[PDB]
Image (cartoon, coloured by chain):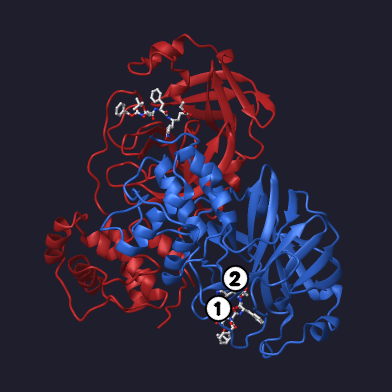
Chain colours: A red, B blue
Amino acid sequence: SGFRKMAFPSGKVEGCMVQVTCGTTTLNGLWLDDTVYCPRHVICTAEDMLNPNYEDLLIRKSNHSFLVQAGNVQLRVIGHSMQNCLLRLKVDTSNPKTPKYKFVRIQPGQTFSVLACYNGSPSGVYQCAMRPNHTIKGSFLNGSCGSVGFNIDYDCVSFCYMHHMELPTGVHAGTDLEGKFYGPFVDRQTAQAAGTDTTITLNVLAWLYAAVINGDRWFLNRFTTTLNDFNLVAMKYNYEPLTQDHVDILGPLSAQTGIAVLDMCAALKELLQNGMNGRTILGSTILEDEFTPFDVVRQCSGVTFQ
Amino acid sequence: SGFRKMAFPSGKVEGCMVQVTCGTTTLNGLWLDDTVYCPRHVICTAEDMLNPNYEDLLIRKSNHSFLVQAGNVQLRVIGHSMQNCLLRLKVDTSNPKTPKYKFVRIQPGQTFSVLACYNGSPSGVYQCAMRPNHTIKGSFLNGSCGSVGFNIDYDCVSFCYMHHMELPTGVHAGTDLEGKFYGPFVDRQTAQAAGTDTTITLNVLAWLYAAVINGDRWFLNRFTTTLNDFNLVAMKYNYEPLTQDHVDILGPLSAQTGIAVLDMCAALKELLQNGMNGRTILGSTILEDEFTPFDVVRQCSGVTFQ
Ligand SMILES: *[C@@H](CC(=O)OCC)[C@H](C[C@@H]1CCNC1=O)NC(=O)[C@H](Cc1ccccc1)NC(=O)[C@H](CC(=O)OC(C)(C)C)NC(=O)OCc1ccccc1
Ligand SMILES: *[C@@H](CC(=O)OCC)[C@H](C[C@@H]1CCNC1=O)NC(=O)[C@H](Cc1ccccc1)NC(=O)[C@H](CC(=O)OC(C)(C)C)NC(=O)OCc1ccccc1
């Protein structure tokens, strides 16, 4: 037993990280087959980060403007294109370590692992959720751009995030691997602020199931709720409204614990209203919202500690 | 910025995981050079887990009693020895993916990354602290034995933990890579309980420095304390006593933030006494004790957000 924020093993992603340099700007890139992906802001001039015109900046570059390094090996750039907010650099060598991979756009509430990288060298790995306001609560310093987020299914890597910026609340913004931003953000240093966030109701509920699977029932109650009555309380506490789809997603967890979803919702409504009374749930004093139902099924025993 | 429980990138360790089978018992092993390490309890008979005599069980085995699998490749066992609570199986092939590595015994309070594995296939990675009571708060199911804990320095892997058991509180026990248990535990299913735990004072303090580096000062106060007066409060709240060595270790963090350690101790004494008043510190409502000063320096900016 136990319950931890668990990241995917990062080795298949480590073998894909390189360093990309244009002038005196260096950041991370992702090398799959004969292509290296990286934030287009690598081509920004030091005094024009406010209003860069990337089409105009990019046409002024050649293939040899870009320096790509994999460990100690220089990879020769032989073609380049811009795709939304990324660059695609074609190189002379196909990555021998390219895993099976897909590019996916993840959805708010879903989680992924981040491989924080600096100068093309991986330094750490942690799990993040895509927030409802399309930011992540990551941990990134200068040099971290081009670090990627991913999930692994069987032996296929689903890349879903490349890192681009930090906003003033200390939260993080970036794109999928087609270069489209998550959220309304743009890759320029003009003032921008994350919209107000919301708590991910489906995940809080999934995590309550985890706590039960793992043997704790203290927070349950004799009550039930309608979906609509629940959502009135949810709006009050800045929780996302719960939908029938969310209820259907909780099906398997519900089945495993013998707890109907709306009974679990009633339990959660009581927690919101009354607090936790100095008690913890899976070691936590707050209601945790960064584990999906998928994450709970992946980590917990298939057998409830009854 | 941001602050996350961050694990080391796990790729160098992934390339070392294998499956080891004796009869109908399968668990994980670690393959370095021409040796595979695994818990000796892989040789336990199904009806004798209470009182196994391992010397007696082991002499009844041959090299071909053990089946070692790396991915789809059978590795032939050609020698075996017991070392404390582990087995060392000599195999026909040296691991081509063996990284630079060391075996280290870590000390209570220190942290490491765990690569949870099942049937020789890595499934997840998370950070753990060695608790003062010599257990870890991990996340492990049946099949997880032989999963390892490690740190990485430059490109050297310091292996420090192999997993062996779960105790009744849902916490975890195991050995270093010489096979000596952390704590008073033994590898038999006879009743055993973790000693009462203590909060890791040095880490709580390191994490308060992190919160300051990252720009928050709300919890500071105008006061100072003596080491001895601090420890009277620490005993009250079940915190480890703070030592001059711990104060000297906080030197660099202290220097970076301009906060004397004993002023930070006074701040912490006020937090223990008064609570947090509904406020959070680096997103947390509890005083977190699983980040070392090393972990904070590794993750935070070298420049304080003043
Ligand atoms: C990665 C790029 C890199 O490798 O290092 C850059 C030298 C870096 C990652 C962040 C740095 C700290 N932690 C991170 O997650 N990205 C950037 O620095 C990114 C570069 C950029 C983006 C677009 C065009 C050109 C260059 N810039 C930002 O993240 C800035 C950071 C910042 O705080 O800048 C100000 C000093 C506030 C201007 N973020 C940003 O511009 O947010 C929009 C904004 C601007 C002004 C006021 C409010 C909000
Ligand atoms: C890994 C071995 C494996 O790959 O699966 C085993 C089939 C496994 C890891 C734990 C399982 C659940 N989560 C884990 O972290 N290890 C064990 O199962 C280990 C096997 C063992 C150890 C020593 C000799 C022979 C076999 N056994 C334990 O961890 C047991 C678990 C348990 O709860 O057993 C009882 C049902 C309580 C007997 N732990 C244990 O024996 O703790 C001591 C104890 C015994 C009796 C009362 C209180 C405490």
Query: From mark 2 to mark 1, how far is it between C-alphas?
Result: 8 Å
Q: Secondary structure at mark 2?
A: loop
Could you classify mark 2 by the number of other residues whose Cα lies within 10 Å: few (under 14), some (14-19), or many (20 or more)? many
- Both marks 2 and 1 on one chain: yes
Task: Determine the residue located farthest toward the right in the rendered image.
Answer: B78
Q: Is mark 1 within 8 Å of ligand 2?
A: no
Q: Position of residue B181 (x, y in %)?
A: 68, 72
Residue B57: tell me if it is visible. yes
Residue at 35% x, 47% y is A130
- B198 to the left or right of A271: right
Note whether A179 is above or below B134 in the view shown. above
Q: Are marks 2 and 1 in contact (CB under 8 Å)?
A: yes
Residue A137 picture location, percent across and down: 37, 45
The circle on residue B194 is 1
Q: Which quarter of the picture shows residue A180?
A: top left
- Taking depth in this image into account, of B143 and A207 the one nearest to the observer is A207
Badge 2: chain ID: B
Is residue A305 positioned above or below A4 on the image? below
**Which kind of residue does numbered mark 1 sit on?**
Ala
Q: Residue at x 57, y 71 (%)?
A: B135
Earlier residue among tags 2 and 1: 2
Quadrant of the frame with the C terminus of chain B: top left
Q: Looking at the picture, tell me which residue is in the foreground, B250 or A143.
A: B250
Q: Tally the numbered discs.
A: 2
Where in the figure is residue A59, as x and y percent of width and height?
Answer: 45, 10
Q: Chain of mark 1?
A: B
Quadrant in which residue B46 is drawn: bottom right
Ligand 2, by image quadrant, is bottom right
Which SS class for mark 1? loop
- Residue at which label 2 appears: B134
